[PDB]
Image 1 (cartoon, each protein chain N blue to C red):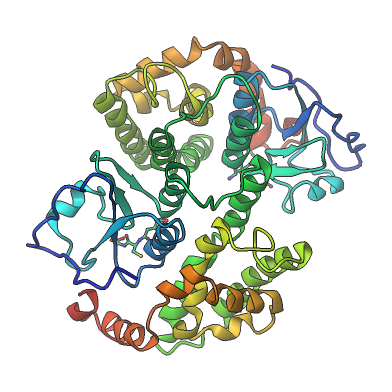
Image 2 (cartoon, rainbow over the protein chains, first blue to last red; image 1 turned 90 degrees about the vertical axis):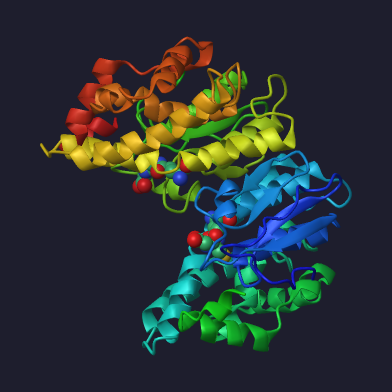
Length: 238
Length: 238
Ligand SMILES: *SC[C@H](NC(=O)CC[C@H](N)C(=O)O)C(=O)NCC(=O)O
Ligand SMILES: *SC[C@H](NC(=O)CC[C@H](N)C(=O)O)C(=O)NCC(=O)O
């Protein structure tokens, strides 16, 4: 919600300076790391501007935002740059008022970061699973590894006996995990959660969250992206 | 300072419960990750107990502190477990009063975490360098890679024109990086900072810090450790 604009690529005008009272995020519509920070921006009700970046043909000026041209990057009114999706999310939460997403209790807050670490293998595994399916490979081994990681997550929800990873209602950790879980269906690996019932309840509960729901990707647009993407078609990155 | 005790290994008595008003850290005298958390414990003047763990022959009960028996682990009076050195350090800083090690400003705090990420390749590279030297390998390539990482760090200090990574005086980020820098000499890779003058000034400045100085390892004990270690001698882990 609010990121439906053409990407800027090589030869594009850099945006103006960030206006006072706004923060800016450099994103890309299909990037799960950027998705994570956009969820936090929305959930916290932060006034912001989304600038999409062309990852195949990056604007030369974009390397002045991140030395390797990665996304997400946050850029403030005072010229300050913040990156790593997790560092970005955490900064957003501390810097801005209203709803607090991380717990106040130091221990509870640490627990969520520990849960974040337990999840660390999932992003690259889902990616490897996708790449395998998209080349026609019998990706039984990667799926088996993903299922294990998801079993590790299931045991947390199951032990805590709460709907969300951080308790009875949604919080920071839930948004941090969300984007890869949204992608399972289109990735073709929704079956990797067939054995994890609390994860499946969590997925349902997440979709009902105002913020999660507002930012849900259109499934058919996303399928088109993946087709162009795996053909290395420049149109994917627009 | 305060970690000069025999390690507990297989068949060892587990320690009692953590007494009210104390936090406990599971460590090992030569572990750089644990060293990081001990520096924070000391710097914050936190009342604590250090329990050393035998990494070659782990106590069976230790898997009830960390599922893979890693260190450091913090254990509280209320039975709570916190791990990952960085998560531990961060929790310590938020939970305990007096001197604050991370900056108060959200942006400045985020910057330090960004500096921590820039440093991320250094631990395993220094380890690979050590392993290479200790088997008699012409480790020119690993040293070249380490030197690059150290050049990346030098440019930060140089751009900021301050002694410490977080400013004119010592702070959290400095303690987080410290342990690998202490180890360069005994590792045999002190020459990998020959080209980085602010890093070398920083190293000198760090050694003068009350906390850093208090926890400095004895060089000859450490050489003995490495000899036993690379011989897979059980005595290394005592
Ligand atoms: S989704 C696009 C890529 N983003 C990242 O992999 C950021 C990961 C960070 N670790 C994080 O923010 O958490 C991306 O920037 N791809 C462009 C590239 O050239 O790598
Ligand atoms: S120094 C001993 C080892 N510790 C770690 O590698 C912890 C690293 C974490 N990422 C961190 O705390 O930052 C260790 O626990 N070795 C024992 C083993 O069997 O791996």
